[PDB]
Length: 68
Length: 69
Image (cartoon, rainbow over the protein chains, first blue to last red):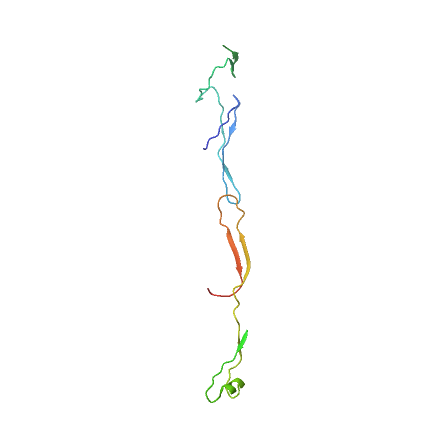
């Protein structure tokens, strides 16, 4: 599908991302990689964010709290 | 390998003298070879070590005779 996901990404710590196009030949293979592209998630431009389900103990990177 | 002898004969010389082969002219000596029958010497299947997918398996059959069809 040309798209894979990391389900629990570290917060505020940047990362260098590379995607490899591994080929396959009859005897062996060979890989051509894309250029490095680093990115970090912050408070800017998330999407598909509808997982805010209150549970009474809301642990967050910005606060840990308990509410009724 | 056979040696063949050619000859002609007339009524002058009978079957008897033909058996004796005297007075009847004869050919020089020529020997001819019989081509051997088609002989198989090796049969074997082989291809490259298949990595993935469908690959052609070849058949190696070896013959050592002589013919034209």
